[PDB]
Image 1: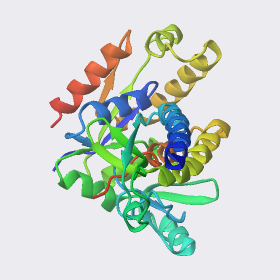
Image 2: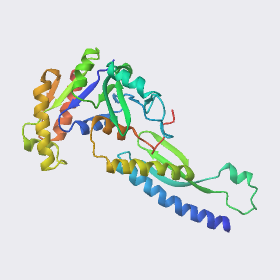
Image 3: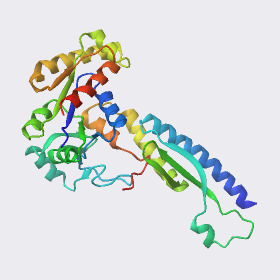
Length: 180
Length: 116
C-alpha cells in the first residue's frame, strides 16, 4: 500500500507532471468517473469510468461518494475514493490534482494522504521558482498561497521551500520517500 | 506508372499530415513521433493488379517514449487528425485552469493507443 499524494501551492502542477513522467513505476494517476461519452481513442476503465447516468452521478456527488467532483464543458467529472484506493494497492503513489478540501476527505476515508504545501517566502520568491509566470500572475499566486496556508495549515504533512524549482522538486521527492 | 504517381502523391500527403500531428502532439505535451513507412494492405493482394504494379501505400509509424511503437494506416492518421485539431482548438480556447480542466487535457490522448 502506497500513500496518495496531494501537492499544493505554486509550481504544484509542474511538480505533479515531473513526478509522473520521471518516475512512472512509483507514481500514478487514478481513473476518474465521467458522464461524457467515450470517444474512439478512449477505453473504459483506463481513460475514465464512463457513467451512463448523469442523475445517478449527481446523486453520488451529493452523497459524498467522490473526494472531488466538477463540471467541465457540460460533463461531470468525479474522483472516487475507490479509484484512489485502487492505485494505492498496486504500490503506486496516486498523484492527485485536487482541491485542499479533498485532503480532509481523504483523511476521513482512511487513505492517509501525504499533503505537501510548497510555500513561497516572498512575491519575488514566486518569480524565482516560477520563472514562467508573469509579474501580474506571480503576484496573485502569493495571495492564493497565503490564504491557502492560513486555512489548511493543519492539513499539511510537510511544507517545502526553495529559491529554484530544482530545489523544491528535489525536496518534494525527499518528503515523499521520508514519510513512507 | 499510374500506381507510381498515385503512391507518390500519397507519400506527399502523408509527409505533411505526420508533420501536423507531431506539432499538435508537442503543443499538448504528449510528445509522439510520426514517421512515414510503407505497408502492403490485403486489398493490394486481392486486387489482382497488373504485374509490375507497386503494392505499397503509406503507413504511419507511431512512437512514444517509454511506451513502444505502433503502425497506423494513413486513413487512421487522417481521421485522428480530426480529433487532434478539435482537442487543440479546445485547448487554445479554454480559459479555465481548474483541477477538472487540467485533468481533462492531461488524460485526452488521441495521439497514441495504449492497446492493453
